[PDB]
Image (cartoon, coloured by chain):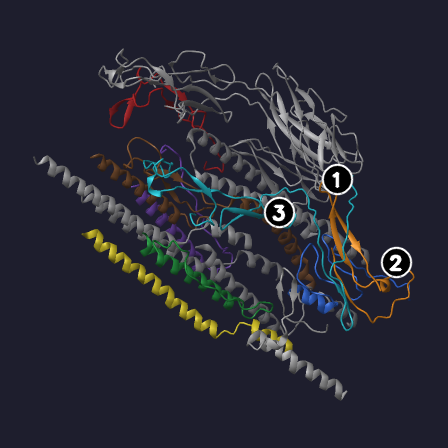
Chain colours: A purple, B brown, C green, D cyan, E orange, G red, J blue, N yellow
Amino acid sequence: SSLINHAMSGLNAAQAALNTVSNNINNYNVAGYTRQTTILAQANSTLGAG
Amino acid sequence: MSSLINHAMSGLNAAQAALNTVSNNINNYNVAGYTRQTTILAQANSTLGAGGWIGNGVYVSGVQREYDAFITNQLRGAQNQSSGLTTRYEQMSKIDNLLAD
Amino acid sequence: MSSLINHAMSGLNAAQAALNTVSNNINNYNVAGYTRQTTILAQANSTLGAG
Amino acid sequence: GATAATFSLSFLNSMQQNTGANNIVATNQNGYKPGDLVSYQINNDGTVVGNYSNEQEQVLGQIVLANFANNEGLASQGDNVWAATQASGVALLGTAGSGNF
Amino acid sequence: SMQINLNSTDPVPSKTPFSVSDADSYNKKGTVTVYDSQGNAHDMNVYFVK
Amino acid sequence: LDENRNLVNMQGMQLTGYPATGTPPTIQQGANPAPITIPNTLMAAKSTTTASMQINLNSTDPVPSKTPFSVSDADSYNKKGTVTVYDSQGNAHDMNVYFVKTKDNEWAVYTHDSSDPAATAPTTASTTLKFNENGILESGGTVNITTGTINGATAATFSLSFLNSMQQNTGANNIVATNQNGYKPGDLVSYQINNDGTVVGNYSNEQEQVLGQIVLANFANNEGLASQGDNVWAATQASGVALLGTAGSGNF
Amino acid sequence: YSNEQEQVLGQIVLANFANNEGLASQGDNVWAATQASGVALLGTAGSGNF
Amino acid sequence: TQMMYEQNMSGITNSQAEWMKLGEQMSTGKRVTNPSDDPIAASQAVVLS
Amino acid sequence: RDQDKQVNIAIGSSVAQINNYAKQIANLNDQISRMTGVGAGASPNDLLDQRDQLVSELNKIVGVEVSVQDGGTYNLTMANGYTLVQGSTARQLAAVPSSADPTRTTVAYVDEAAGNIEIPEKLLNTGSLGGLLTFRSQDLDQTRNTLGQLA
Amino acid sequence: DQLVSELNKIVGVEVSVQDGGTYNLTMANGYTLVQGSTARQLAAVPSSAD
Amino acid sequence: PTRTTVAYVDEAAGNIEIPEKLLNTGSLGGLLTFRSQDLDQTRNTLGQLA
Amino acid sequence: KQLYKQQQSVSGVNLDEEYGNLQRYQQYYLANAQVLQTANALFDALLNI
Amino acid sequence: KQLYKQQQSVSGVNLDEEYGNLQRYQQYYLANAQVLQTANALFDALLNI
Amino acid sequence: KQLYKQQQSVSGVNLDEEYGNLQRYQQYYLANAQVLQTANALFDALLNI
């Protein structure tokens, strides 16, 4: 449930970040390629839980 | 009595809530913007009543946002100072490189 | 008591901090102005149980 | 537009050297500006001490502890907090130096 | 209160008397800050000579 | 809450309590308890009628070049304070405060109703303020503006004070406080019940209205109370009759 | 738009009720209007009580 | 945890930047280049030029 | 002069940047206000964190004191004592080439009383954009005119 | 401490630990440099002497 | 008065310089002895030569 | 950076510390589970008569 | 040449921070895996009863 | 030069004792972590009861 949802969504973010770093470090030498960084953010935390 | 079942189950609720706090703590540790969130919960201590020390009063209080607001705003001021000094020194470097040439 | 885990976490934290300190002795090394920084260790405070 | 301060300025502990070298090093002064800052610390016994926008220190604060004649007698039924009982004796107040704290 | 320590064997300077920026007619500058009736701030500057 | 938004038990038996009435809504003991409800309504048009701000200042500023201040005199006044207000229809006005000074333990103030294009900025200092060498404000604590009527709304009127400031021994002109009593109206999305028995709602003006408190019964002999089914007691001669008090009323 | 341009058209209507728990579900992930629930109160997202 | 990563990583960065400068001077063969290499004597260099 | 126009363009963009941050801060302020109104003492600490961190982000561009409303939200004060925000509302800031000395770009800010300013750049001591401004004023202009004087 | 060491290496100076916007920082003529906000700004001048 | 030496401050009466003959110990006693014999005697010898 | 270090020392999270917190709560949960198990056992035992 | 140095000093990809990020997110991923497995384990420990 | 070196003697990082220390404390950190696992086995056995 929500705890597993936390576990996984963070896994999604980690995978995305790894993809980004691999992308950049591989593309590193190409003329015209600018470094790129991937950013994180919190969910639509909204309340009905007390 | 069988409320023990309930009682224990309130222990389960406390554990689940503590777990979710732990989960958000761990999952967001690297997010640009986050603060430690310690879980809080009560005890069936010596508040007066008419039952004695029965399992009356253990439950989840909520979660705090552990951030030094005082040094946080002071930090924003320090960021203003750094902004100014860093900005103008970079603009300096721009000319400096040509006199380097 | 939660002592069993707490001993370990105390020592773990202390070791990590001392690690940071000795690093700080390494990371600067060459730069003039620095002086070597040394660390202190001691027992935890007396929640002494019953003595 | 404020009062022109008047004061006594004392050259305490000056000395003359048959064979020495010269310097002026000391100052005592007993005035300070209006304070306007949030800055304080708590230390070791429930007393509270702070540094201030006068760039220096002050001490102001203490937290009072309580103990009873017989510890285990308290009210014993709820909520992380206690209440006194006749069996336990009414509170004796103190701060932590006198054995019972 | 401010303290001064000196050596006795000095060739007293030839300024009769001292002047606020005549450098030979003072030796070390000591300073005393002060605050008036209910806490407005001031600082006082001093000169000393033999 | 039923489709009437009246508070009821599962059978529909009403939850009674003491109501809040008037403005500000206050729990009136001078009534008898009745069913409490939640009207789906907006907040009262709480106009601004008072204000206060605190001004801890240095009184050595030399005469600014472009005195007097009226409109754009950015070389005439030394510090800005502001307090936003609401006319007596409940709409939005803002007040702006401007500080001008050549009186060496004192300060003088300009003001304007800075949402009002019909009124225009007064070209003269609206009030003068005083301090003593003991680092303390002494007097000057009054000024009023009537937030000018524009769109057929009644203009509101307020009075403003500046009490108990401390003096900044040199240079550091400062101002820290904000007070004004009023707020615009706003719709309701909140309802909370608390430990004291009270019931509060909160409104899109970002402020509150209270209407509700729950009152409890107490008896000389509980053994007289008789269940009528549906977990409801009939207060009986055998128990005495109800003595009423809310939580925190000593024995409740 | 396939011609480097944008248009906006769309907004859905939301419902809020006097007696949420009273809401008459039909099963199959749906509810319906009734007296006991109170008549429907409409709105747009984020607005007021929505 | 951030502080530790930043500490050691920036240690690497400043160690590199130091080496970079030594590398600059060594490779070029000039001890002085610019206001950042000589805010003072370069003026006398102009004079002597 | 290329560098001159660079600083002009940069400040022009910075205007939009501050306006965007103001809008975002106002939006989140609305959110926390309404959500704590519903909350009954709720702790949407994540919302709190992003709101105040976004504020800290804006501060760098122009030194700020994020002045508080009673419980919920703020009104935004620049370091000089000027202030432009109300609850969930953020007013506009605009980019203008100067009418005072027309070889520069500058910003415009408005008080809803009657009109907008072409900002008196005397005010602009705040960190980033005032960092650019001090460069332009003392450093850039002095060397510029020294060069021209010698030529 | 390193900054004051270099400041010394360009012009002789005293160095002893204290504060008050000031430091034990006398220099070549008994005059004192650093105090509060008034850290003295010296000048390059044509010489009345020559 | 050329020298510094160690004392116990019996604050009911004042500072009493414990005679230096007594400080035989390692670190502090050794430093005191080092001045007493080595440095003062060596400067005396240097001056006698001169 | 010093101010950042201290603010983060309050605010940040160490992976080590939470793993320790994680393990405790496993103990807490299983302890409560044991409690409910024994309660179930006694419940049915009582009902046996 | 100089302005190119500016452009690439701001925009270019490195090897250092990418390396550090690779490890930091490797660690983050493994930690979230710890969460996954231990959480399901606690759920199953409950589910058995 | 002599007196600068005399200052360095006390102040200067020596790079050998520190390196040996770096190893020594890694061992300590491992000792701590492993000990935690042992307590885990202890309350594992207690739980399994």
Q: Nearer the viewer, residue A40 or B52?
A: B52
Q: Are marks 2 and 1 on the same chain?
A: no
Quarter-of-image position of residue F246: top left
Please give the chain letter of the residue carrying mark 1: I
Separation of residues labelled 3 and 2 (CA atoms)? 38 Å
Judge whether residue B56 can be spotted in this image.
Answer: yes
Image coords of residue I45 (percent x, y): 44, 40
- Residue I100, labelled with which disc? 1
Q: Is residue D13 left or right of residue D70?
A: right
Q: Local crowd at mark 2 within 10 Å, few (<14), some, or many (≥20)? A: few
| Distance from the alpha carbon under mark 2 to that under mark 1 | 50 Å
On screen, F108 above or below J10? Answer: above
Question: In terms of image quadrants, where is residue F63?
Answer: top right
Q: Amino acid at mark 1?
A: Ala
Kindly tell me whether residue B101 is visible in this rendering: no
**Quadrant (top left/top right/bottom left/bottom right) for the N terminus of chain D:** top right
Residue highlighted by disc 3:
D52
